[PDB]
Structures are given as C-alpha cells and as structure tokens.
Length: 123
Ligand SMILES: [Cu+2]
Image (cartoon, rainbow, N blue to C red; front, side, top):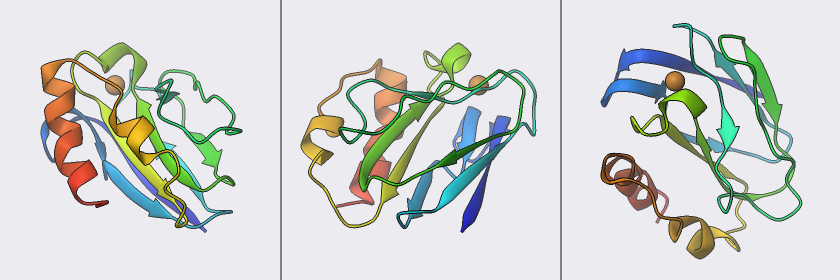
C-alpha cells in the first residue's frame, strides 16, 4: 500500500516539515510525497539506510513515489531545507540491523532535536 506524506512550508513541528515525519511501512509499501508547497524534495541522508537500498534524490517541487523493499530504518532530508530541519524517518518491516548506525549520524542542533522524538517513538 501507499502512504502520502506532504512537503510543507508550515506544519506540525514548525517551518519546513514533512507530515507525517514518522512513517511505519511494510516491505512492498510505497510513499507518495506530495508537493503541497513548492520548493521541497526528498533525498537519502547517507548513513541512514539499510545496505542495498537505492539512493533517492527527487526533483524539487514534483510529486514523487518511493517504493520500499529492504526492511530497516531510513532517514530522508529535503535538500534545500536540511539546515532548517526538514527530515523524516521511515521504518520498514521489523529488521533493526541499521538502527544504531542510523541514530549515530550527527546533524545540526535543530535537525537533531527534530529526530530525537522520532527515534524515541521507534524504540
Ligand atoms: Cu523543503
């Protein structure tokens, strides 16, 4: 099945957010990222993906679909707004092999503060 996530200038958590910012999926699920507001994309954050997953880098302002097959923890950023904390976390299936790795990637203060509660909600 396919879950929609909106790319927003203003939403739950403040400026430059994905809503929802935490997505639980099953292997085979897809997300459709909706350009609610223009000027957003989705891109893998290196070190925040199970080994074998393809690198994602979408075109700014377009709807995009990402299908998920490998189980594990994925972190995605909005490229132009990463410094502004626009990030999301995707959990696929039950495998948590890459969790300690993904949680160990460092970020600016603002982005870190956003991820904290998401990680907390996966533990
Ligand atoms: Cu953005």
